[PDB]
Each structure stands twice: as structure tokens, then as C-alpha cells.
Length: 34
Length: 34
Image (cartoon, rainbow over all chains, first blue to last red; front, side):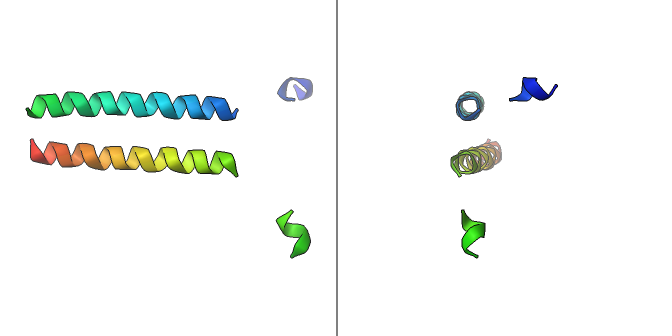
């Protein structure tokens, strides 16, 4: 357990993916409105 | 004081959280419009 444990790019990628998904959802909502 | 003082991930996380909050507010505004 001690040896196994011994990051930023994962955070960047997750943020980008979440932003893209949110933008897609917002675009779908806008299309529904229009 | 000198010893205590001696970052990027915090900036990334704050940006992601602020973007998510802004997207949620925009979605709420769009729902109000529609």
C-alpha cells in the first residue's frame, strides 16, 4: 500500500469535458426554446 | 512569518467551479425565457 501511492492534466481534461457537455446541454435547451 | 510563506491546481479548480456556476445560471435564465 505504501509503495503504490508514490494529476493536473486529469483535472484539465475533466474540466474541458464537463464544459463541453454543459455547452451541449445548453445548446439543446436553446434549440428547444427556439 | 518568513518560514511560513515558503497554486496552479487551485486556479484550475476555481476556474472550473466558476464556469460551472455560470453555466447553471445561464441555463436557469434560458429556462425562464422559455
